[PDB]
Image (cartoon, rainbow, N blue to C red):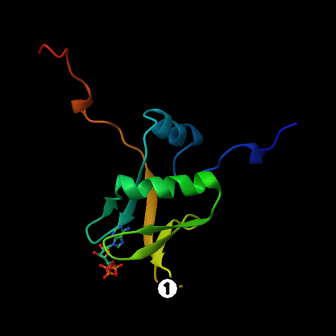
Amino acid sequence: PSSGSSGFLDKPTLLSPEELKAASRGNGEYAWYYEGRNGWWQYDERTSRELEDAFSKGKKNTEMLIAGFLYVADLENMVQYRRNEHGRRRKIKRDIIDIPKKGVSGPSSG
Ligand SMILES: Nc1ncnc2c1ncn2[C@@H]1O[C@H](COP(=O)(O)OP(=O)(O)OP(=O)(O)O)[C@@H](O)[C@H]1O
């Protein structure tokens, strides 16, 4: 016996199933982002680990604290909003780190 429900599934794209998997498995890292004024900006490692655990637990939305506010992170539509707000919402996403050249170096003697 077997099923398509025995594995994970990704959001839509213009790429292929062998591209999305390769972008992830080529490093095995992860990060979360949200749309600010000038583009996508990364969450704190304190915070993004809570978002990363929520889709792994099975919940459809989780909660997080910031500079002075509680934001509800919805995993279904990939957005954030305040607990009292039903309509107005800001975009979030998952992404992967590629690692800089600073990750490669010689022996401790030089
Ligand atoms: N995902 C987030 N992580 C951390 N801080 C956030 C996040 N979303 C909002 N903030 C910050 O919390 C503060 C208030 O956010 P709020 O959503 O009220 O801003 P806003 O006035 O609606 O912004 P804008 O109209 O520019 O989108 C701002 O300093 C904002 O950058």
Q: Residue flagged by tag 1: what amino acid is it?
A: Glu
Q: Residue at x 65, y 46 (%)?
A: 8
Residue labelled with disc 1: 85
Quadrant into which the N terminus falls: top right
Quadrant observed for ligand 1 in the rendered image? bottom left
Q: Residue at x 54, y 53 (%)?
A: 53
x and y, in percent, of residue 71 in the image = 44, 73
Figure check: 29 above or below 12: above
x and y, in percent, of residue 20 in the image = 52, 43
Q: Residue at x 41, y 59 (%)?
A: 47
x and y, in percent, of residue 67 in the image = 30, 71
Q: Residues within 10 Å of mark 1 (few under 14, many from 20)?
A: few
Residue 11 visible (yes or no): no
x and y, in percent, of residue 51 in the image = 49, 58
The picture quadrant where one finds residue 104 is top left
**Outermost residue, right direction?**
1
Would you say the beta carbon of the disc 1 residue lies within 8 angstroms of ligand 1? no
Quadrant into which the C terminus falls: top left
